[PDB]
Image (cartoon, coloured by chain):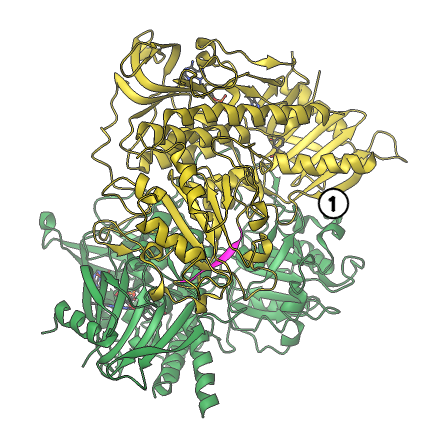
Chain colours: A green, B yellow
Amino acid sequence: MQFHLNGFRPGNPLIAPASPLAPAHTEAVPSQVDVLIVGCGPAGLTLAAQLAAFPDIRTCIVEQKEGPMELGQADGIACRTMEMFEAFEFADSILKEACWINDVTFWKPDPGQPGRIARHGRVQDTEDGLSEFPHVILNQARVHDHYLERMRNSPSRLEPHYARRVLDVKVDHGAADYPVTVTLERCDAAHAGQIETVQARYVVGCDGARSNVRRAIGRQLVGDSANQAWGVMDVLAVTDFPDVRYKVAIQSEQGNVLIIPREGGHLVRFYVEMDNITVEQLIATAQRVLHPYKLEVKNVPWWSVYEIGQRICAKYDDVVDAVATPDSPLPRVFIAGDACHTHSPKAGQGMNFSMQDSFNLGWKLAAVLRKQCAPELLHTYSSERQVVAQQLIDFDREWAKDPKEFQKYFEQHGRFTAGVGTHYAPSLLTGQAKHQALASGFTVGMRFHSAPVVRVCDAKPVQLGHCGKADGRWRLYAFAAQNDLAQPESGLLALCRFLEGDAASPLRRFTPAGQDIDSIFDLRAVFPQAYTEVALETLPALLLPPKGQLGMIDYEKVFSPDLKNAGQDIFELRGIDRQQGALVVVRPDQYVAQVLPLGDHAALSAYFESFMRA
Amino acid sequence: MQFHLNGFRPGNPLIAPASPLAPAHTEAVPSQVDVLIVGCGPAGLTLAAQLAAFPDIRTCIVEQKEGPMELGQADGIACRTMEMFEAFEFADSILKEACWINDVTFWKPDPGQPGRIARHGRVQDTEDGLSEFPHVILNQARVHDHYLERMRNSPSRLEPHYARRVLDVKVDHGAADYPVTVTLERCDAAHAGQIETVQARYVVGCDGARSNVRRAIGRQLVGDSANQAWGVMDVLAVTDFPDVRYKVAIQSEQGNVLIIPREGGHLVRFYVEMDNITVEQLIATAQRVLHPYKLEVKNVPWWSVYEIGQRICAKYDDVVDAVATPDSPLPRVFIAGDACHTHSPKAGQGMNFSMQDSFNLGWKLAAVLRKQCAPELLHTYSSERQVVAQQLIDFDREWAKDPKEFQKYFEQHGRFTAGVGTHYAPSLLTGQAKHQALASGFTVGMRFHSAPVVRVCDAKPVQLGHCGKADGRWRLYAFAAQNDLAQPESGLLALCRFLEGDAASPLRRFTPAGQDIDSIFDLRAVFPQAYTEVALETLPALLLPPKGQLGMIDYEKVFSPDLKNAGQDIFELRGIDRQQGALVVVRPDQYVAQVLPLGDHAALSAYFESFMRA
Ligand SMILES: Cc1cc2nc3c(=O)[nH]c(=O)nc-3n(C[C@H](O)[C@H](O)[C@H](O)COP(=O)(O)OP(=O)(O)OC[C@H]3O[C@@H](n4cnc5c(N)ncnc54)[C@H](O)[C@@H]3O)c2cc1C
Ligand SMILES: Cc1cc2nc3c(=O)[nH]c(=O)nc-3n(C[C@H](O)[C@H](O)[C@H](O)COP(=O)(O)OP(=O)(O)OC[C@H]3O[C@@H](n4cnc5c(N)ncnc54)[C@H](O)[C@@H]3O)c2cc1C
Ligand SMILES: O=C(O)c1cccc(O)c1
Ligand SMILES: O=C(O)c1cccc(O)c1
């Protein structure tokens, strides 16, 4: 992290100075806002945390509950989700508190012994090289706590307006501004029944399975009925079952159970398959399933009956057209998370997929509100997120049931549950991949698979993808050709010359006057030479850019590979064409948009000209 | 970290429940306390943070300054210091905010060019395998902030009594209890001149170079005059000097300068050698030294003239006897940090050595106050800490000046500056090492050099030494012999049987009735077999101990080596005798006290009987 850019600032640097652009939080909900977010669940808080970074945007998030939750329903945190948490700068804390899932063990009835289970298998939960983060388990409420802290400490000093139930949402297609009218009812005793009305430019329903926003815009969850029903209980118990601290799938003649070890080393969650349910019944069933192993429950902090069918909305916004074109009406209301797609418990997605909906939408709304991107960009939210959620359902539709074909489905299921399987098809934002071989390890349309590199300014070993923070900026990862440092006339250095000095450059065309040169496009250069061979003093100013009020130099734009440790060279690991180099264009949500030749300046310009505004 | 032991507890688990044993903080300093700590510098806060973990002990820490500092004088954080920060559970946060020192570069005059410097060398700052943590740089104030937060969130809810200047300390050798009388003067305007008096059982002067506590007990810093004088300035500047983000030693005909890159990527500290100094003069000198590289200073958050000689007290307590025996008077007042030893700027110790003084004393004071250890244990504070500080001075005394002999001194200097060179000589606490070959990598008298292992309960890869938290507990790391799992009649399992069931066992003799079985002795077993081969259900209850009010099982006492990654097996890395196994006894300050045969139960008992109380 970088700080003290404009002068010494005492205290925790993660606490940003309050921006004068963001009015102080008021007891009453403001009369007009840029974005009204409905629901403080994972989807809403992810979106709020993202928008909190932009104090010039007036964001209001409402929640019917009267305050933050202390114990949540979800607890699974996927590898790709941890990568997003790193973008929000709190992955470290989650890693220290959460229960890591390293192995998953499988138990089944013992062939030579009646009414007893025995261990039948064990698998490494996350395949080697899949992600730099592990899969972990942590009370949903703690994730909310981190987002709320991020919102509070942001320049916006954003905090929720609790005890507010959104009753209706209406779009006035003839309105000049703030065309969306939201009606809310105050739920606390002190204001019970009081009605509040808010006018907004955009509204996002992150209000869950029974979303009133979805209903307001006439969308409906289409799918199959509750495929199954699960009794779920978080317990503090004593057992002699040896695998209780692992994630465990148990099949027995007494019923099926899934064990999810919880944060703290003691709490454990049991999913008991079912279909007047009491916790006593759930416990009794788990005991019968675990026999001969004993289970003595001392305390049950929470339990419930988790049952939901797989359903999905045909569209995630208020635009009727199934597939939008340049003449379709522009969207004003969006729905994210469970409000538009519910995945069966089998899917194993938990709250992970819902938060990716918000991470997709956040930067787009910010860019459009700031007049940096055409409103048409907003159509890509539904077209990207609805499609991948439906494709996921199609897969889990069949995954619901040769021996090497099963292992294949098992492996794919692992990539999907880890959240790294998302692959957007060609579109306004995603290329066709005709130059994929320039960087074969950075698949166009998929998330930027981070790899180690060494920072040239100080030899620090770092993960390249961690340059991608949740600050709304696009990233340009330029991997230099072998002779680029020695031959500035072409390749990487020529690209830099073009970006900084050519009027047609997207950097010159789209970076607002007066802002830092890397405020829209975050360019990072990676050379194949050892860090000791890259002379910073000889590089273009674009790669050692001054920024802020004092013109301080940003020394973190230049990297080399890890050449000390065998097999850790990113050019090898990510299949970079060494003789040609490659430009990997990454969106603010960390998804790869393009893999282009370093010298195709015209294509780079044309890409951004297609949706950004000068 | 483990939590929810006695029931579900919402919020950040690092915030402990307030103990009813610790009275609330009062505006006035209490009239009587167990421990009075003077000074909220690194030494005092380290000690306070340690004692804050024991709510049954009444600790009061006073400081003449009126509040916490925002910008400190020291900034170097050594590898061994990071290991202690990990023991206090905040190393993670420091790693994310601090500026890592990966390489150190050296610059000297360019042979073929007048008045100009050129790079002459580069070295990896921390040798491979030295520590699991890097050497980092971070504003002293931020370290204080972490300790203050730890103190505040501890069960004791400990916070300093600011604006108090200790004027005198007197020991009444005829007093029945609280024999030490401390006189304090309130410094704030509101109480300017008001005198407060506190009676304490023990007083620790962590009041710096001009310590009033040291003066009160007649001790004096003996040594040489200021060997040198350094102009020090923390600046936000723009330079084209290529190595500004590295730690850099610069020698030129215009003067000598040391560059220390600071947290945040922009701030930089310059030490300018000297001997009416103004910052303008310091800047002018740095510019002349850096020529032809330019240095344009935009802002100077802080600067000063750091000049101190190498001095040390002959003893760190109020006991006259040079070397205490069983008939010497018992100590009541101790001095730590700069109050008893000042190391030249060349030493490169910063605030690191001072905090180790407190980490040495903390657990000893707690054990004595709790009547768990004989008061004689307190003599070991001075005998251990004064000796290693003097030996350090002797070394830096000669280090102050064949070519392969210089590299030897350079390498040793590196181990010393990283803080891992401390090696206590045989004593009441430290053995002779006649069984050192049982575990050659765990040198008796030196800190426990952590290595990777795999936790059996959940296959989590962890650092074994991180079991050693700053909670005052002794650690017993038992490395099993090859056949121990298969032959319980001897070796590790027989040791467990002895520890839990034999009346002469130190565990049975010294663990207070009613407390958890691992409340004094934290036993961790490490087997050479893969984690998948260690059946938890077959192990003694001592290795899967129930604890707390609900009898929840602690699943973190059993480990195996990392056998997945080549060359990561701790039995190989730390030279464990595979056929014999080894018991490594580690003190609450992470220093190895003994390396004993697993079967020498008599020696284990005798060791603890020599200073613990039943
Ligand atoms: C009873 C129950 C048990 C569950 N158990 C599990 C489980 O065991 N494992 C698992 O993986 N997942 C479980 N889930 C699902 C998991 O909690 C969700 O998938 C996840 O929370 C979805 O995230 P989200 O952001 O889309 O919405 P949600 O988490 O559903 O949050 C929506 C939010 O919007 C608010 N809201 C709704 N309507 C309005 C309105 N009109 N006005 C204002 N605020 C409104 C809600 O109060 C809530 O805070 C469970 C869900 C429920 C309801
Ligand atoms: C002007 C100055 C510049 C320095 N510059 C550097 C540098 O550039 N680099 C470096 O590595 N080190 C530097 N140091 C030294 C570094 O700050 C110390 O080595 C480190 O702080 C020592 O830790 P300590 O805990 O022993 O005591 P200190 O940090 O000295 O703290 C002692 C504390 O006790 C308090 N105190 C003292 N007397 C009393 C009393 N009678 N009653 C109550 N409270 C009292 C003080 O106000 C202070 O907070 C500098 C020190 C000074 C004074
Ligand atoms: O994170 C998971 O793997 C998971 C899968 C199912 C339920 C659950 O709570 C967690
Ligand atoms: O941490 C260091 O290596 C160091 C050495 C000297 C001065 C300083 O501030 C820091």
Q: Toward the viewer: A436 or A228?
A: A228
Q: Which quadrant contains ligand 3?
A: bottom left
Q: Name the residue under label 1.
A: A537
Asked if one can make out residue B335 in the rendered structure from this viewpoint, the answer is: yes
Instruction: Count the numbered circles shown.
Output: 1
Residue lying at 72% horizontally and 25% vertically, measured from the top left: B398
- In this rendering, is residue A551 above or below B599? above
Magenta-colored span: B451-456
Residue lying at 44% horizontally and 13% vertically, measured from the top left: B213
Image quarter for residue B279? top right
Q: In this view, does A227 lie to the left or right of B520?
A: left
Q: Toward the viewer: A129 or A238?
A: A238
* Residue B453 counted in the magenta span: yes
Picture coordinates of residue A169, whole percent (x, y): 23, 65
Image quarter for residue B200? top left
Q: Tell which subunit mark 1 falls on.
A: A
Residue lying at 76% horizontally and 64% vertically, measured from the top left: A482
Q: In which quarter of the image is the C terminus of chain A?
A: bottom right
Question: Which kind of residue does numbered mark 1 sit on?
Answer: Glu
Within 10 Å of disc 1 (Cα), the crowding (few <14, some 14-19, many 20+) is some
Picture coordinates of residue A69, whole percent (x, y): 24, 55
* Residue A523 counted in the magenta span: no
Picture coordinates of residue B582, whole percent (x, y): 50, 51
Asked if one can make out residue A218 in the rendered structure from this viewpoint, the answer is: no
Whether the residue under disc 1 has CB within 8 Å of ligand 4: no
Q: In this view, does A188 lie to the left or right of A329?
A: left
Q: Is residue A600 left or right of residue A218?
A: right
Q: Residue furthest bottom?
A: A402
Q: Toward the viewer: B179 or B210?
A: B179
- In this rendering, is residue B433 above or below A147? above
Picture coordinates of residue B470, whole percent (x, y): 41, 39
